[PDB]
Amino acid sequence: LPRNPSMADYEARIFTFGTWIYSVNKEQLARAGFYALGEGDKVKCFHCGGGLTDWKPSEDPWEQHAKWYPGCKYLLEQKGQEYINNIHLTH
Amino acid sequence: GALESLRGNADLAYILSMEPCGHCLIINNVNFCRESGLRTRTGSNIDCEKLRRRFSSLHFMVEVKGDLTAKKMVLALLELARQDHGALDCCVVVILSHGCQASHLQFPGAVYGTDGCPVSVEKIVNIFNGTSCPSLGGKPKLFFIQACGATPFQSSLPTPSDIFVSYSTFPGFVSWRDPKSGSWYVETLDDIFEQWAHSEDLQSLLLRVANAVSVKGIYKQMPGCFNFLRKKLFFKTS
Ligand SMILES: [Zn+2]
Image (cartoon, rainbow over all chains, first blue to last red; front, side):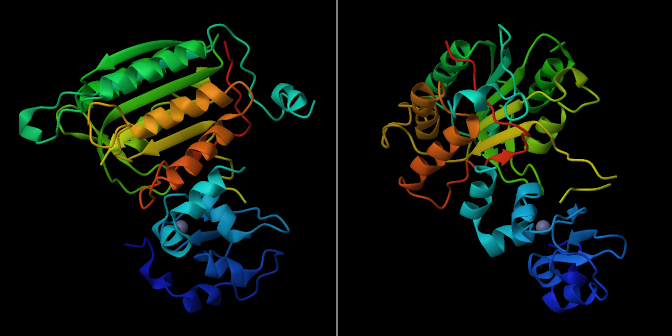
């Protein structure tokens, strides 16, 4: 079960990125399960609850999500175990 | 060369120059209480001996502690974390036992003590934090578990750090019909180390293992390593 059931749907998540002024694409972030918290470029995953901040220019939300929260179920559901392990086995 | 300047680059690779390299604790659970319903893990003794020999040759002071209850596994880990690693470059924990799932966003999984009581990988890993063990701060803390079945915030700082967990639940035996032949995953890991530790870092070694596990079946292929190392780890070979 997700830590934030209200953000289980992509539409609810992208909504929170109303005025997003950062380089990291908000659509990608939302697809990767993230939703903006309202302060800085801070986002959290609706399922695992993991938060990420200080995003870099060409940084992929999914890679960052797998790199820091390899145990996320949404992550596993969407990308599969092979993907997660490979992210961790090729830093 | 390209491989020589990477091994030495103190910015890219952990420096493992001390002799001994560090402690290596191996929890080897073979016999479980009848009541738990967990089967005797025959073949584990040979898995243990392979790893004990492996890390000894990698310069670690290996200590084997067998048949530990959940509580005693924790005590043994707290004990290891409570020691002074000031003169060591790395720490290694190896757990061989039955296991079960335990959800966690960073270090999922759990292992059973001989009593059939679970100990999550998260608790095991966090025993070695920079507050309880500053002595191992900035030093690789490796965990190899065979359990037969942007930046984060709150405060912006990279954590976990210098933690590497290889968690395997692959139940296969070297000899698929003989449960005493030893764990296939352990053998594959030992084999890869014997042939590549001298020239390849931990990540590459486990990638080779994952590659092997892959052509063996795969639904498990869960050695699902949780890599939070900040630099490449090249072991100190004989
Ligand atoms: Zn997540």
